[PDB]
Amino acid sequence: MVKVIFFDLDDTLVDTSKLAEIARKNAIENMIRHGLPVDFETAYSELIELIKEYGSNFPYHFDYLLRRLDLPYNPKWISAGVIAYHNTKFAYLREVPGARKVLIRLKELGYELGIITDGNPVKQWEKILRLELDDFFEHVIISDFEGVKKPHPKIFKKALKAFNVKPEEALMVGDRLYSDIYGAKRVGMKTVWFRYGKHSERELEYRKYADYEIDNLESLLEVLARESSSNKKVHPP
Amino acid sequence: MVKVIFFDLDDTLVDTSKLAEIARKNAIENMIRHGLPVDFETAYSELIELIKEYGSNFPYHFDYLLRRLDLPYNPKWISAGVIAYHNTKFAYLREVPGARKVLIRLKELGYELGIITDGNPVKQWEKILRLELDDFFEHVIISDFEGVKKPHPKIFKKALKAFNVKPEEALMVGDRLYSDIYGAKRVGMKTVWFRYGKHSERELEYRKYADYEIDNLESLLEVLARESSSNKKVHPP
């Protein structure tokens, strides 16, 4: 008996990865527009390699890109990249196609909704408030408050307790088979894998933990309607 | 004709990983000594999991450990961990066994020595100065200045240029088959893999790039003496 539907935030409700990609491309293009003496293909390829070598959250990608290209520190070029990166984030932040329409319909149907995500609480809430997703959700469960990262069972159990619902009365929708799907199924929740983006072979080994698979968020409505034989019921282990 | 010998810093000349392990264990033990209501085995296991979930350089491991254990923020326990962690680093920073004796002998024999490493320049130099390794090396090549990470060829080529030596006139000694060995061999240097610590199957696929393998730093002297048929010579591609 599904009463609560939980969603991951990034790449399920919000188009985070795609936005990041476009922001990075625009950053390089703006650096070039302002003088960076390198072609886009070369500069962007090096940025990607730099990101894989130094990490996604390294604070000096643009400064190090200049070092990598044997160019002297140039605050003009670096600022050009930062400006374009931020401008992109400000202008294109958006929901994954169909997300809002689906949320509105779920509320119209009477489901209670929640979010289960990882990351800095303020940053995650910024996405929620900027996209006006706030009153769609009764609770926003963030793993960092609990000192764990999904798929750790602690955060999923906390989500269930917040809504005071049994595992089988909850359904998790997420794009990541390991962190979202396996995590929710391990504690007894129903699961819907949103096949969005690319997945590694290791991640795909967790595909069995998904009760349903959808390529479009709209299809979630079909799944829930089908779940009209209830979930399974009381019974056993 | 080996004229220059290059060394990686961490886990080749300096016992970095082992020191970090002991520092982490001591941090947990000190937290417990000051009240942390958890047994060492449990607390340390969670710390390790926390490190794998949040990263080696996350600045709030101890704060998040409390969150993970459902304990209220306690600055006393956190400070106890920080104190023990730093005390350990201060008291036990040391060379990998045999490193200094080998460096002294290499200088006595007439080799020019250099370091090729990754990381924040100031932090790497702190290890060098604290262990009084300074005048053993003519040049300390740090990848971050070049905006790349080993095994990128750029940093190895820079090292060769600094010493104005041909690739075959240089030999690289390092514990990592991918970042140290493959990196040096790719540009033409002679290589000695120091089998220290654990190595993954993927790393082991680069074992062919090592000309020699040693389990003790002292054995490097034997390798160099053997290299008494020169390296190979002028010749071809």
Image (spheres, coloured by chain):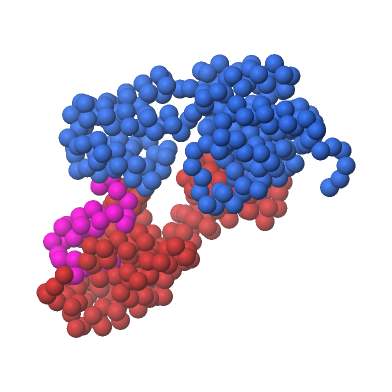
Chain colours: A blue, B red
Of residue A16 and residue B170, the one placed in the foreground of this image is: A16
Please give the range of residues in magenta. Answer: B145-172
Which residue appears at 53% of the width and 58% of the height?
A: B22
Q: How many marks?
A: 0
**Magenta stretch contains residue B151:** yes
In the displayed structure, B170 sits above or below B62; it is below
Which residue appears at 48% of the width and 30% of the height?
A: A16
The picture quadrant where one finds residue B187 is bottom left
**Magenta stretch contains residue A185:** no
Which residue appears at 49% of the width and 56% of the height?
A: B20
Q: Position of residue A121 (x, y in %)?
A: 56, 28
In the displayed structure, A52 sits above or below A123; it is below
Q: Position of residue A237 (x, y in %)?
A: 84, 47
Q: Position of residue A50 (x, y in %)?
A: 33, 44
B62 left or right of B108 in image: right
Q: Position of residue B94 (x, y in %)?
A: 42, 62
Of residue A112 and residue A160, the one placed in the foreground of this image is: A112
Asked if residue A70 can be seen in this view, the reply is yes
The picture quadrant where one finds residue B78 is top right
Residue furthest to the right in view is A235
Asked if residue B175 can be seen in this view, the reply is no
Quadrant (top left, top right, bottom left, bottom right) of the C terminus of chain B: bottom left
Which residue appears at 20% of the width and 55% of the height?
A: B158
In the displayed structure, A146 sits above or below A87; it is below
Of residue A154 and residue B38, the one placed in the foreground of this image is: A154
B139 left or right of A157 in image: left
B92 left or right of A68 in image: right
Quadrant (top left, top right, bottom left, bottom right) of the N terminus of chain B: bottom left
In the displayed structure, B47 sits above or below A171; it is below
Residue furthest to the left in view is B234
